[PDB]
Length: 280
Image (cartoon, rainbow, N blue to C red; front, side, top):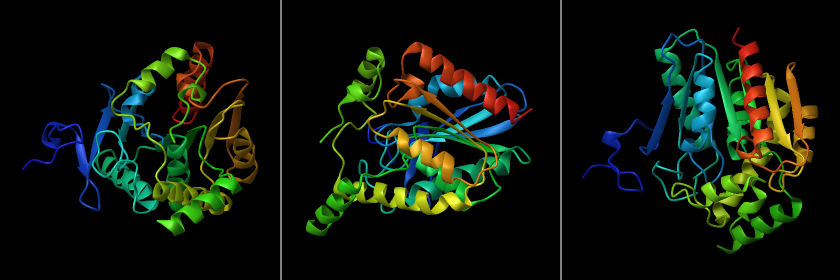
């Protein structure tokens, strides 16, 4: 029987990779017509998938970068029980597999990471695992903090064995409508086991910051109810990176690349400038 996505599409008809655990991950590529100047991996957040980055990847491809992504295990069109991971390091391991395959085909090109929310934590842990390997990282509202109340709560619930209000994702109501009707997004409540893995990610990010030296651009909304702006200020202070920049979007919510048009246009522009300056 042919292996199929959770939506029943055969993987033989789609770009994919098989991870170290034998699971198929759905892949996406946005390649320039000419010879690329750099590679960039796009790392999506919890519950979402790589297709959400279509416009951002098309902007990056227009700067002569070869953009690539995959749906993390348990997400989008990739295999695995929905929003379940045996250990958070599976996500990092899989990004490194994809990155190594692309570097084999495009040797000598600098490689960048771009991550949003959990995807940002995966990007930080990926660059920390290989110091000096990546040319830069673009983080949009990365997951770097965990409430001490939610932490002790999840630990007690794990010893024993509710969905997000979409309106907190963005002030752009059309973007909230798109999010609520995308069948590849998991809008279910957090499973206890997955909550424990997000706590593991936050702990690992904390320990990684003294060894994090990759250049980075950090974009954060001041009114983000999912990833408190306090974490962006702490990440700026605690990362050892010699090239670090923070931009705060006053009044903006969590999904900065899908926010009010004035915010989204600035986010696209600032990522374009930052990546353009570091691939010149």
